[PDB]
Amino acid sequence: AYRPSETLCGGELVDTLQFVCGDRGFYFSRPASRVSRRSRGIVEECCFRSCDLALLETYCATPAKSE
C-alpha cells in the first residue's frame, strides 16, 4: 500500500482526535480489560489496526444544544 503502516497510538492518537474534531470534543476506547469485554474503540482500529480519516471522524462527540 501507498499509505504508511506506522499506526497511531498513545498521545498522538489523542492529538489526531483533537485535530480532526476540533473544539467539538471526541470519545475514546471504553474497555481496557484483560477479561472478555469486547466493544469498539479508537485504539482498536488505529493502533491495533490502522484506520482512515473518515473513520476517525466518527468518534467525534455529539452536538449539544441549549435554549
Image (cartoon, rainbow, N blue to C red):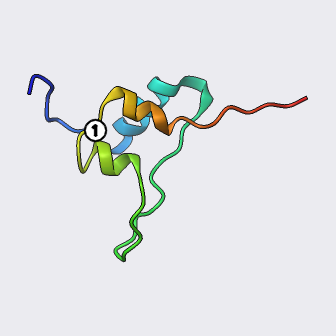
Residue 62 lies left or right of residue 12; in this view the side is: right
Q: Position of residue 17 (x, y in %)?
A: 45, 33
Where residue 31 sits, quadrant-wise, is bottom left
Q: Is residue 43 above or below residue 23?
A: below
Residue positioned most to the left: 1
Q: In the image shown, does 4 or 38 lie closer to the viewer?
A: 38
Q: Return the x and y of residue 2 as percentages of the image width and height.
A: 10, 22
Residue for point 51% across, 27% down: 21
User: Which structural element holds mark 1?
Assistant: loop
Foreground pick, 24 / 52: 52
Residue at horizontal 37%, vertical 38%? 13
The residue sitting at the right extreme is 67
Residue that numbered label 1 is attached to: 8
Residue 37 position within the rendered picture, expressed as x and y whole percent measured from the top left: 41, 70
Type of residue at label 1? Leu
67 vs 13, left or right, is: right
